[PDB]
Amino acid sequence: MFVPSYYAAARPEQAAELVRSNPFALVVSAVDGVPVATHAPVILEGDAVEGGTLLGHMNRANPHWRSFASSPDVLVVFSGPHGYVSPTVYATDPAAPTWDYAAVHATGRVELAEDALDVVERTVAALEAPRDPAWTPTPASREYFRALLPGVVAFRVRVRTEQSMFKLSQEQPAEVYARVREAFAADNPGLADLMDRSLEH
Amino acid sequence: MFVPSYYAAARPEQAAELVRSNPFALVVSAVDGVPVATHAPVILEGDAVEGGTLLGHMNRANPHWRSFASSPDVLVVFSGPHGYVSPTVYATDPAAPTWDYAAVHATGRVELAEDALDVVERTVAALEAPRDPAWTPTPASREYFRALLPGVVAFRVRVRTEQSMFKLSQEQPAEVYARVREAFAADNPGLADLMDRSLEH
Ligand code: HEM
Ligand code: HEM
Ligand SMILES: N[C@@H](CCCNO)C(=O)O
Ligand SMILES: N[C@@H](CCCNO)C(=O)O
């Protein structure tokens, strides 16, 4: 990922906020020069992405994790709100379309996690916390988690580098930008909200 | 990506449909064992993903494409609708949460495309076609496209292998499945629609 200057994060906490808000990530390895990717829920431990630790799990039947045992470098992609930007919205000419989005790419060394029950229980807690009502596992469900453990593989990534893209129409003049934000306010409020926070500081 | 049997596509056209419907893709290379990824619009040429050709573009200032000149194998990830599945919706116990999603992973040999204007013009046509009204470039905008060309790099992927995941609650018993579909019908109609099509044949 390349980040033009005008799409860079305005604050270092913006990257961590995106990661926490969008835990359904893409975990990517380079198995002997061939990229392999798994979609998996991944949570953040720490205040910042760079230097932080990511925790996730996948299916034991998914052979991807067997590439982790050597502890190679992996890439974890977190994707926030996104949406196609049509020049119909710009109301200007000439023009070209684009796609608006935010994402965090975290790269670091993967390792298998022995404490898989802790990882999955922390993932439940993180993903249910913003819901009302939130689901709390019954004691029977916690026993079910224990029974499921032989079929899961948990892992940690120690993040060496972080890059963040906030591609949110900052390349447009102010009158056009306002039109884009108004259009997403109806069609994609999560993206409009992200545009608003990107202008902060 | 690993695809359990009950999440496999029911029809071979399902993968192509997802690709056409979700052109904002992730292009992934293995630059000397390190995964690198760029978010870019990618369109499909052909009736099937496997054996088909993908066409995309990226920023020339993005150094990712300089890894393509040797024509390595790349992975292109197309992501359809997705959403967190809370056990609150299941109304059963014991239970564990999951994430529902659909995706197509296309792997093949990348090559730079000299015909960049054709690629970007076909991308405009594909992404505007489902809109009403659709944006058609003015002659002035087509000249603007020509003026932008030195700053863009277009590329082709010849897809050798395709895998498709339709992880859409098929592991749940029928009464629970019905509850999931009803909940997404309100919260995420694109995902509910995908659940409906997954049961076809
Ligand atoms: C918010 C909570 C959770 C989410 C979003 C989630 C999501 C997922 C996803 C997307 C996969 C597929 C990974 C792959 O393709 O390799 C998976 C696999 C798996 N997870 Fe979770 N999971 C959650 C909680 C749990 C818990 C609490 C356990 C308890 C041990 C668990 C155990 C498993 C197992 C055994 C598998 C592999 C087989 C299966 O799909 O049932 N997960 N999970
Ligand atoms: C549906 C139509 C289009 C979409 C969704 C789209 C989207 C994008 C995206 C996401 C990028 C950033 C890629 C990266 O990070 O490396 C990009 C870059 C670029 N694209 Fe497009 N594009 C479209 C049409 C066009 C057209 C018609 C042209 C005309 C030549 C063009 C020229 C460029 C150029 C010059 C760049 C790099 C600098 C810039 O961002 O302006 N694109 N495009
Ligand atoms: N940044 C230029 C060209 C964008 C082409 N890719 O989206 C514009 O906004 O007109
Ligand atoms: N497939 C099991 C466990 C799912 C855990 N990961 O989502 C269930 O649906 O209960």
Image (cartoon, coloured by chain):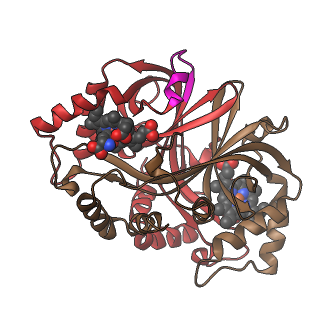
Chain colours: A red, B brown
| Viewer-proximal residue among B49 and A170 | B49
| Viewer-proximal residue among A173 and A4 | A4
Residue for point 39% across, 31% down: A56
Is A16 placed left or right of B56 in the picture?
Answer: left
Residue A115 sits in quarter: top left
Residue A127 higher or lower than B143, as above or below? above
Q: In the rendering, at what x and y percent does residue B128 appear?
A: 64, 74
Task: Using the rendered image of the protein, determine whether residue B135 is visible from the camera's viewpoint.
Answer: yes
Quadrant placement of the N terminus of chain A: top right
Is A141 placed left or right of B24 in the picture?
Answer: left
Residue B71 sits in quarter: top right
Q: How many marks?
A: 0
Is A134 placed left or right of A197 in the picture?
Answer: left
Q: In the rendering, at what x and y percent does residue B23 appear?
A: 62, 60
- Tell me the magenta residue range: A63-74
Residue for point 78% across, 44% down: B110
Residue, far front: B201
Is B97 placed left or right of A5 in the picture?
Answer: left
| Viewer-proximal residue among B62 and B90 | B90
Q: Is residue A72 magenta?
A: yes
Q: In the rendering, at what x and y percent does residue B130 appear?
A: 60, 77
Residue for point 56% across, 58% down: A100
Q: In the rendering, at what x and y percent does residue B13 appear?
A: 61, 64
Q: Is residue A141 magenta?
A: no
Residue, far bottom: B133
